Length: 240
Ligand code: NA
Image 1 (tube, rainbow, N blue to C red):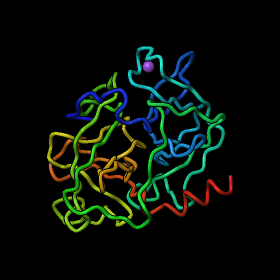
Image 2: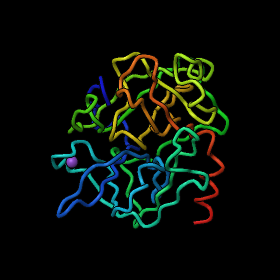
Image 3: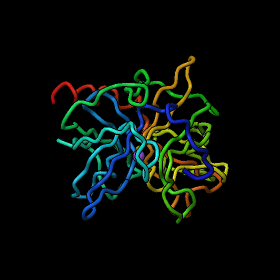
Image 4: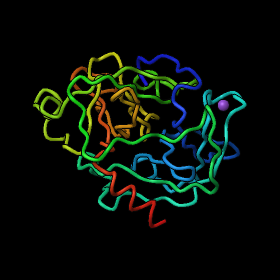
């Protein structure tokens, strides 16, 4: 997250770190949201690679023991059937991971609350992106979980020529684009939390930013719109 601030350690208890085995150690690769005790929602493009993955819940600092982490292997990966790795702009950038064990809930580990199906945020709605991604374009991952305030940019605007044009679809949410704050590599698959009727819900799964850099004016960060996939998510979980 570029232009972010350190999160309080109990602010976003549904945030997870998806990590992959790198030699004798593990490395953060993207984010995700805990949606059942044994299911995680992330971006399809995060699990394109044939790696060994684990999920870490209750994580705050990637490089220090927090005393709150639970580490659980990934048992099954279900990517959206329409996903196409070389066409991120076509959408369907979403995947569900079934965990090897069910995690225990506490003040650091809670299920993410999903929006009702079909819900679309009005222009300029207050949202936070969270994650451990790069803190500057071509920079390095954050140590501690970061959060940035990113107001939504509605489809009519985001799909105009000076923003994203045709690349953005109705199945996506855009947020930010002020040129100071944004998502960045390592944030993919992580949540966009939006305050609706007094309750934060996860409205987006971070999907892409501009190749021209993370925080670019009028290239808001693009998220998969979770409310477009409520039935898909239910169907996968019900059949696994
Ligand atoms: Na830690």
